Image (cartoon, one colour):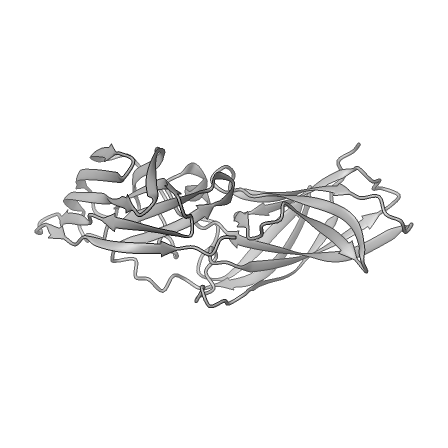
Length: 300
């Protein structure tokens, strides 16, 4: 019946788990595990009271469960539902409820482990652009909040191993929507671009969701190759269920044109994009460098 704050009281560790699928400890790479400390006082907390954990800069939880319990020595003191930020908010959260228990306690403390990935960009969306500025390569402080309480720990995020000079592509599963976002950034031109055609044709069983696209020019890219800003500029586009195509003109120096779209896949773990990738740096000659990628996912 009341909302209480300050249940979560420490950020004990943030560690990345290396798997066969994932090779470098990037912020968006599954899976990061945040171990948090929590403490409840029965004189200030009653069963049915609620409290929330805030995770700034966290895209999603990597789990198929809808909730996680705060438990100690086999007793469930609270149930916390996952509320991923995704493309809706820059932060994810837990919404928790204090559980009734068969033990009486005055004070009890424990930890919880949260499987997450961070959002450092992915599209021209308001959400991704803001989060694109969340972290830099190297040492960072990751802060979560419960009401006015701030809890933090340090972590070291490797920069992308992919050169930001060439074309950039990225895809990311949006669990609540059963969709992915997918991004193409045009290769860099030193002194802007005369012209270009950027986008992708979907195949196998992928189709483009034309109601959720972003076309922008970004002022450079962050440490993970993602747009940090998005401004309009001179282009025409055509979006159909199988292809998004953006023809552009007269982009100035210092900027990177990009395009991103939501994708609906018959199989969210396997689809194919064919990328047009044509561009004519200013004062230069047209490059026509199409290529195809198969995107593979390990969603459960």
